Amino acid sequence: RLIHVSRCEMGTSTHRCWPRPCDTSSDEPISFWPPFENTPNVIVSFGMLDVDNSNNLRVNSSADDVTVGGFTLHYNSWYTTTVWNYKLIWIACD
Amino acid sequence: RLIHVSRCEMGTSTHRCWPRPCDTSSDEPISFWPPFENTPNVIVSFGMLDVDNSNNLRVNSSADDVTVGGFTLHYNSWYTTTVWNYKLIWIACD
Amino acid sequence: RLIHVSRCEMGTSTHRCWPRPCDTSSDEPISFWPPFENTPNVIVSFGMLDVDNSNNLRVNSSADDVTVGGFTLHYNSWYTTTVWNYKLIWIACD
Amino acid sequence: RLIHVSRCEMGTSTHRCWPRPCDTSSDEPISFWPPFENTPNVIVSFGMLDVDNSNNLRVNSSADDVTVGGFTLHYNSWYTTTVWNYKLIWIACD
Amino acid sequence: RLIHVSRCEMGTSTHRCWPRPCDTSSDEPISFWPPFENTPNVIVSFGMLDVDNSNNLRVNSSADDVTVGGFTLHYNSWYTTTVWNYKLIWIACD
Amino acid sequence: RLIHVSRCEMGTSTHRCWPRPCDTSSDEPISFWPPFENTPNVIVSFGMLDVDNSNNLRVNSSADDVTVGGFTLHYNSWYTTTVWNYKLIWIACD
Ligand SMILES: *[C@@H]1O[C@H](CO)[C@@H](O[C@@H]2O[C@H](CO)[C@@H](O)[C@H](O)[C@H]2NC(C)=O)[C@H](O)[C@H]1NC(C)=O
Ligand SMILES: *[C@@H]1O[C@H](CO)[C@@H](O[C@@H]2O[C@H](CO)[C@@H](O)[C@H](O)[C@H]2NC(C)=O)[C@H](O)[C@H]1NC(C)=O
Ligand SMILES: *[C@@H]1O[C@H](CO)[C@@H](O[C@@H]2O[C@H](CO)[C@@H](O)[C@H](O)[C@H]2NC(C)=O)[C@H](O)[C@H]1NC(C)=O
Ligand SMILES: *[C@@H]1O[C@H](CO)[C@@H](O[C@@H]2O[C@H](CO)[C@@H](O)[C@H](O)[C@H]2NC(C)=O)[C@H](O)[C@H]1NC(C)=O
Ligand SMILES: *[C@@H]1O[C@H](CO)[C@@H](O[C@@H]2O[C@H](CO)[C@@H](O)[C@H](O)[C@H]2NC(C)=O)[C@H](O)[C@H]1NC(C)=O
Ligand SMILES: *[C@@H]1O[C@H](CO)[C@@H](O[C@@H]2O[C@H](CO)[C@@H](O)[C@H](O)[C@H]2NC(C)=O)[C@H](O)[C@H]1NC(C)=O
Ligand SMILES: CC(=O)N[C@@H]1[C@@H](O)[C@@H](O)[C@@H](CO)O[C@@H]1O
Ligand SMILES: OC[C@H]1O[C@H](O)[C@H](O)[C@@H](O)[C@H]1O
Ligand SMILES: [Cl-]
Ligand SMILES: [Cl-]
Ligand SMILES: [Cl-]
Ligand SMILES: [Cl-]
Ligand SMILES: [Cl-]
Ligand SMILES: [Cl-]
Ligand SMILES: [Cl-]
Ligand SMILES: [Cl-]
Ligand SMILES: [Cl-]
Ligand SMILES: [Cl-]
Ligand SMILES: [Cl-]
Ligand SMILES: [Cl-]
Ligand code: NA
Ligand code: NA
Ligand code: NA
Ligand code: NA
Ligand code: NA
Ligand code: NA
């Protein structure tokens, strides 16, 4: 019979930048082992955050170039925002 | 034999407001197709955030009215907070 | 045949502290019923957040002591950060 | 994702007739608990057989009235055949 | 997590030959739709049989050339055996 | 969520004896690798059979001592029955 089920993989990525401010952006190659059967959906959020109040809080994250074999874990702030630390979390399921 | 398995669905919703401030709240209908066999659990977070530092950071998100066919993706700030941009992320599994 | 499937459990934990500031840290024991077959991965993020702008934003969360039977849902801010309210979200899949 | 899986149930039914000849036919109600999600297919054969050589060997079996709740395990010989003992086997899968 | 599951397909094939003896052998192509993910095992037996006592009972059956797409349902008697009617049953699982 | 699925294993076992009569009984250790998670059901039938017509046809088969690790594939004729060749088939599903 036909049933709908998912396989999920998940992970975190910690960036301890301070005493230096974090790079404006980061892109990390993540690999699924073994590859998924179907191209999975992937979402990303923040597990930890250390942002300076001297300017607005601007943070962004996403999963780019998602394939059955992996994806690019992306982060970026912009303009005058100063980020001191952060931890991205992500989950991918087909 | 009896085994525990999950089907998962996930998605994101971007709100680009600036030059205008984002509305105090938003409620968006999300449909699952096909419907889940069981009422899934759903959780919501933020994938992107642009908040003004001139006041406290107040953000809230939730999955309301969750059924096998979908749910209401909810967001709200409150009091004096000013939000310029945000992206919600959500995942539903049974 | 051999296939990859996941079982997922998820939940949220709300802390309203206002007008008192939330404790610097929190640790909540979470149970998985029934226990997982394999030790799951767990990720944690924020569903709601209320942080004072008088100081930098510093929030941290994680799943600690993860077993098939459960885990410790952990939160903490640090230094001078003042947090007024927060809601943690978590998802665990094997 | 969509996958093909089967749930299977199976069983045997022994008929010790000797010293009397087995009835020309038999029909036994079989129940699946719990019921299947989809009507299963069912096949039936012989695990044991004791047939007289004074006439031709004529045996027949089938799964009749198959529903998600169960089916009728059917057996019959015909004409001049004499059967002294027999055991039916069956398996149902969706 | 990794788990062992099977998909099964099954079927029957009736050969009514009387008043003529059945052919010494038969080979029928069986198609699996959709094809299995992995090459399944297949076993074959007799659900009905009508054999003349004037000679020894000799019957044979098997699943030949098994692939994910199908196989050849084979039957044969040999030597002096005379078969009047028979029904084959088969089940394929991966 | 909870679903019913089976894992199945199957196999055949050929005994060529002619021109000598096959033994009155046979018992073969069958191993499931890897073991099942739950004690499976097992049914056994005949895929090939060669019985002398000088006496009644008497054949018997079963799966004895079934565990998650394996079982004893049993066969026996009785009294004056002469069996020349036979092939057992079996399928085990949990
Ligand atoms: C957050 O990161 C995503 C991923 O890189 C950015 O997405 C790009 O957005 C531009 C328009 O702003 C599109 O033209 C590109 O196609 C997107 N690239 C990818 C890889 O999808 C997004 O702009 C970022 N958001 C902010 C505010 O920094
Ligand atoms: C975040 O949004 C949720 C959902 O809109 C709000 O939840 C309500 O909480 C009150 C108690 O404070 C309950 O009595 C209601 O039943 C909840 N509504 C729903 C639909 O569940 C929550 O109050 C909001 N948080 C903030 C800080 O605005
Ligand atoms: C975020 O919380 C995690 C988990 O509570 C903290 O991890 C600890 O880090 C220290 C050293 O930094 C280790 O000695 C501990 O063993 C870690 N605990 C666990 C259970 O992993 C992490 O330091 C916290 N981050 C911040 C900025 O507070
Ligand atoms: C074997 O048993 C099956 C099931 O009772 C018999 O099938 C019936 O066959 C007749 C024609 O011979 C049909 O009219 C009926 O519709 C069939 N019944 C069902 C439930 O399918 C079959 O005839 C038997 N074979 C022998 C040789 O006895
Ligand atoms: C039953 O049919 C099968 C399939 O046609 C026969 O299998 C062959 O058996 C010989 C002798 O053991 C092997 O060398 C061949 O490789 C087999 N061929 C196939 C297609 O597997 C089997 O011999 C038949 N049994 C009888 C008694 O007729
Ligand atoms: C068929 O084989 C089974 C299993 O080997 C035999 O079952 C035995 O039956 C006797 C008498 O009824 C019992 O004392 C034993 O305890 C049974 N053993 C098992 C494993 O259950 C059965 O007798 C055989 N049938 C024929 C006709 O030979
Ligand atoms: C009425 C109202 O919204 N009050 C809010 C309170 O809920 C809390 O957010 C506090 C600290 O930021 O700021 C205000 O007092
Ligand atoms: O066995 C051969 C032949 O014997 C009788 O004639 C039966 O009526 C037929 O159906 C067939 O079984
Ligand atoms: Cl840390
Ligand atoms: Cl700014
Ligand atoms: Cl954006
Ligand atoms: Cl404020
Ligand atoms: Cl709340
Ligand atoms: Cl500060
Ligand atoms: Cl018996
Ligand atoms: Cl006859
Ligand atoms: Cl028929
Ligand atoms: Cl002969
Ligand atoms: Cl052979
Ligand atoms: Cl006899
Ligand atoms: Na960095
Ligand atoms: Na808006
Ligand atoms: Na608190
Ligand atoms: Na009877
Ligand atoms: Na024929
Ligand atoms: Na032997």
Image (cartoon, coloured by chain):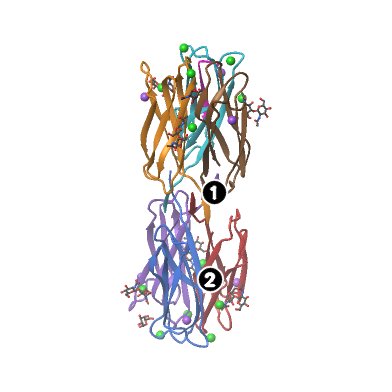
Chain colours: A cyan, B orange, C brown, D blue, E purple, F red
Residue at the spot 57% in from the left edge and 38% down from the top edge: C41
Residues at marks 2 and 1 on the same chain? no
Of the pair D58 and C80, the residue shown nearer to us:
C80
Q: Quadrant of residue E73?
A: bottom left
Q: Is residue A89 left or right of residue D37?
A: right
Q: Pointer 2 and pointer 1: residues touching (CB < 8 Å)?
A: no
Q: Quadrant of residue C15?
A: top right
Q: Quadrant of residue B20?
A: top left
Three-letter code for the amino acid on which mark 1 is drawn:
Ile
Of the pair E15 and D27, the residue shown nearer to us:
D27
Residue A47 appears anywhere in the view: no
Of the pair E70 and A27, the residue shown nearer to us:
A27
Q: Is residue E39 above or below residue D25?
A: above
The crowd level at tag 1 (other Cα within 10 Å; few <14, some 14-19, many 20+) is few
Disc 2 from disc 1: Cα separation: 35 Å
Q: Which residue is mark 2?
A: F86
Say which mark, if any, is on residue E3: 1
Quadrant location, the N terminus of chain A:
bottom left
Say which mark, if any, is on residue C23: none
Which percent across, then down, holds residue A75? 49, 22
Which percent across, then down, holds residue B57? 49, 21
Secondary structure state at the residue bearing disc 1: strand
Residue at the spot 39% in from the left edge and 61% down from the top edge: D39
Part of the protein shown in magenta: A22-30
Three-letter code for the amino acid on which mark 2 is drawn:
Tyr
Which chain is indicated by disc 2? F
